[PDB]
Length: 111
DNA sequence: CAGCAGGGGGCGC
DNA sequence: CGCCCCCTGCTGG
Ligand SMILES: [Zn+2]
Ligand SMILES: [Zn+2]
Ligand SMILES: [Zn+2]
Ligand SMILES: [Zn+2]
Image (cartoon, rainbow, N blue to C red):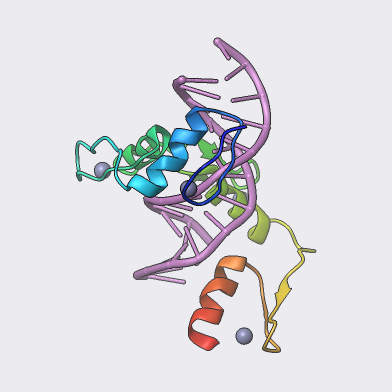
């Protein structure tokens, strides 16, 4: 396949090789028409443009909610509409938390 | 919890 | 190749 002479990243595609170079060169973006924000991937600039519009194409099929991202919509389904969900214990504490996002910020200021 | 973006991979065109 | 989605930290109410 293809290789990266910087971080030893491999990918079978040429476009995904240039996408990895955006993370090393820094800026290869376009610009935003309303806040001058600049994102490398063309898709992320499209979801940034979704911030300034009431476009929420992701709907919760249960409570008919609306979200700007599928993953954000996915979390709402996971923590608010499912009961028997596997929570996570702390490797150095005796508390139990739901999300890894909470686990990441927990170890930041607790450990 | 939600909102947000950064780093990928899947998959059709 | 190009569009969308995935999981991932991160932040504030
Ligand atoms: Zn690299
Ligand atoms: Zn903007
Ligand atoms: Zn819901
Ligand atoms: Zn802990």
